[PDB]
Length: 50
Length: 50
Image 1 (tube, helix red, strand yellow):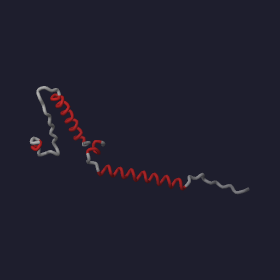
Image 2: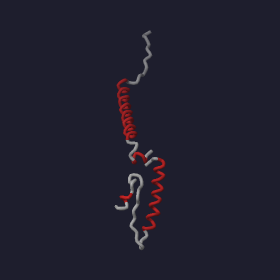
Image 3: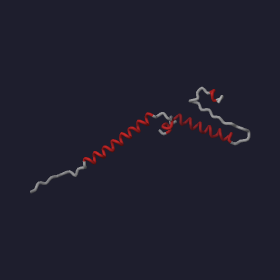
Image 4: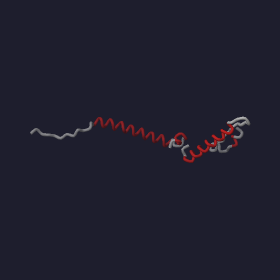
């Protein structure tokens, strides 16, 4: 009765790491946008757009 | 320029200048559009968008 395992069909770890790197890069870019928007909240051009 | 230099609130109050004559149609259209734009500028100031 050869032993029967039960392995999970796992998500690759390098793929997860690459996509997490890309999404944290996107998140820090979004944060930089939030900063450069909230620092220049007084120039009229940025003030016409809520 | 001599009239504009009488404004002590140059950075706050806008002064409009129009040169008129007895034979024109822009004399009456100017003020029609000018005050419409003033009203829009005022309501944009009130909301703080500008």
